[PDB]
Image (cartoon, rainbow over all chains, first blue to last red; front, top):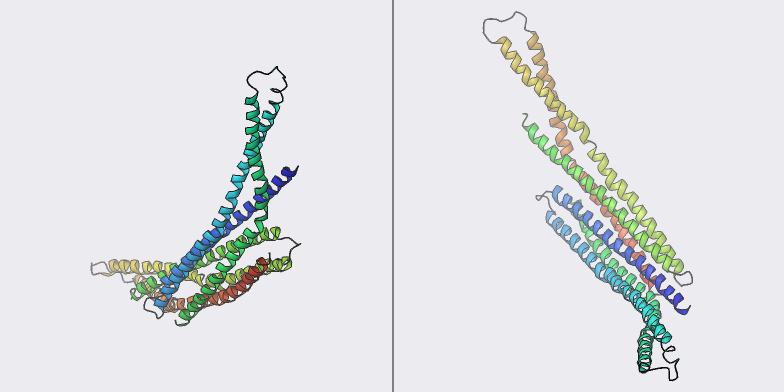
Length: 198
Length: 200
């Protein structure tokens, strides 16, 4: 009951992180498509503009700086948004497995329970294998107490981390975009001036 | 003669291939804007879903996402009219031109055959005919028909060739002007977003 709804918490958390991660991944790669299409255009432009015409050199530098700006914007997005999501969502495969192993080690603890009520149900009916049962149950309890006690504190910590990570991620994007726009703005002006000189 | 023509025809073929290509990269560019638009919309919808109406900034976020969407849209409509359809009006002039040049090639074939079939008829091999004013009337007509047309094009092609410069200026100044507002509006929204997320 307490778990099943907490695990329930963790799954909605997983599905949500996974939808976000996917959306970010799509965005990155729309940035690459936007980059690509801008590179093609400035090359056609670089071609249709004669090397004799004034500003042909400044045109060369715009095409170049356009590119270094897309590349840099793309790279930083990949680190600061996509990779950060990947670090974040990796936590979910580890936990899915930790919950798989907690489902087992409690089946063991319960059978080493089942087995020690039927080795000790024997006052003088028991032989040698009596402390071997008590040692077993104790190893099955310590195994499950660690995994469950450590799992019981870890899930909610992880659930509560979700907002901080979304916040870090979206400020990182805004910072990158802020700079990218400002820089692109300068080049946009330079582009107009070069053209105005034909 | 058909050699100022050749250079003018060269020039035109460069211009036409240029316009076709720029036209394509401009259309492609607009696709990619739409792809960005889309991808951003999908990002902001997941963010809206995550963002609780029980939270401060929720309404402002609903406006960011909203205006964000009107910007992309406006920008797309305007790139369409000012860059893509501006090129469409421009490259479209190339149909008439290409059909007039293909037509001027036929008429120079009308010329070249006339020159041949006048020269057999006429040439002192003792079978002259009192009335081949008829090979004269035709092959007079062939040359005046081809020379006029050849002439027309020698006037049109440079006028049109040279106009490529204004088109390119126009189109890139349009885009540049458009980008200027778009970056500035996008910046504001990008800040609001930064602020709206830093309250969480």
